[PDB]
Length: 477
Ligand SMILES: *Cc1cc2c(cc1C)nc1c(=O)[nH]c(=O)nc-1n2C[C@H](O)[C@H](O)[C@H](O)COP(=O)(O)OP(=O)(O)OC[C@H]1O[C@@H](n2cnc3c(N)ncnc32)[C@H](O)[C@@H]1O
Image (tube, rainbow, N blue to C red; front, side, top):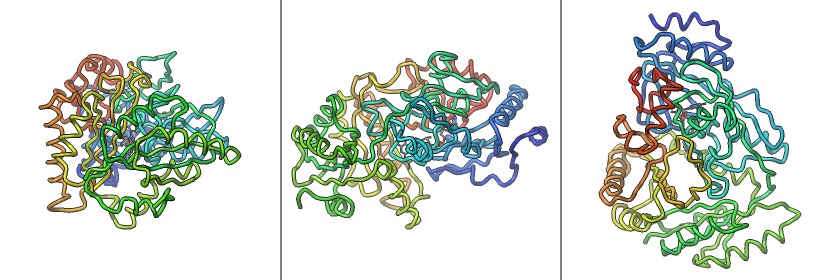
């Protein structure tokens, strides 16, 4: 019995060794791996003691440790088959401090909760994810990208300090100035080098309102050229995203329920915001008029709405409530998330949207560019080698057991896109990747593999951490 000395640890919290089903599923709703135990930590010391114990067993133990955030992983990345799942949200509380234009947040804290606290001081983080009900540790283990990344970089570019429990069970406080290799390793590190128990996030003064804008384009070339010009301009919009709309009719009528019209085939939606304060509405109106005057969208499709900063940032939670009401939230999510270099974007769009795809009815297609200069080259993040690259997110649901959608249909369409990228040398890199072999991961990492592998031996030599990533099998190094 390897799990009886685990039950002998004098934890601040406790272990669950039978009631473990909730930790054997994720948002992907496809993979289910029953863990042997679930740690509900009462402190970071509990996490460190659990990791130290597993490490003390050496190479003769199949025990693994997976930190679970909000479980938004799509293919078992936060699960541990016959291992130990650490419920990071058990430490949410509790150690949330705002000081000096920074917020110190537990790793298991949701971004929505970081924002609610921070707003009480008139402050907020600068860089977001589209959905806020995700943990600080979970999004930083990836990158955390939204409409602000073009300017502030991803969330991983807006963190100043991390408190980590390494795969050796050591508790380390790190930053660009102390234990910097661990700091940079953890950022986009896919949970490979340790568990982030606390993060210092940079803040900026928060606006009270946002002018939220949506416009349509018929031409991809003009759509993307306008996005690229907006991401390079000075005093531009505060959020820049885009959507690919395949076949769908009554798009302006769907917007009419929330947005004010001004005035009443593959289409492209450009989504923008301009941050503002009530006492400075006229300056915003003038600045927005100027910015829009340089764009080439279909004028009759201009829709806008004035909302609070919180209402805009938490917008996806409204869609979550509607899906939960229709029992459409916990369905399989066979998402495909790609990073496409600027030089390949048109060739990609021609084949993917013009040929491979017939409709976009089972989920949105995100498409927008970012600036590579905002991403630090020392992290574990994998990005294309061009100064401008695009995030392309195929955020599909599979509500059907057969036919149109249908995990088998979504999976076939995803394979076709990836096979095209490979055959036509697009230079694509996947975001939120789910490779099953170390050979597929070596190719993904490419020139950055050696760095990733050396950091792994340094911080998790026995490969105890985040086995669901499938990069390093237990004790394989
Ligand atoms: C479900 C979802 C995801 C999502 C999104 C919208 C929805 C509805 N919108 C995103 C967006 O606009 N931009 C973006 O960059 N990502 C977006 N995502 C994906 C999301 O960021 C990720 O799924 C991410 O993993 C964060 O979510 P979460 O907190 O749910 O974390 P997890 O899924 O349980 O675990 C992720 C991996 O990291 C390891 N892990 C978890 N917590 C930690 C800590 N504290 N320290 C170290 N590693 C940790 C897990 O073991 C797993 O491998």
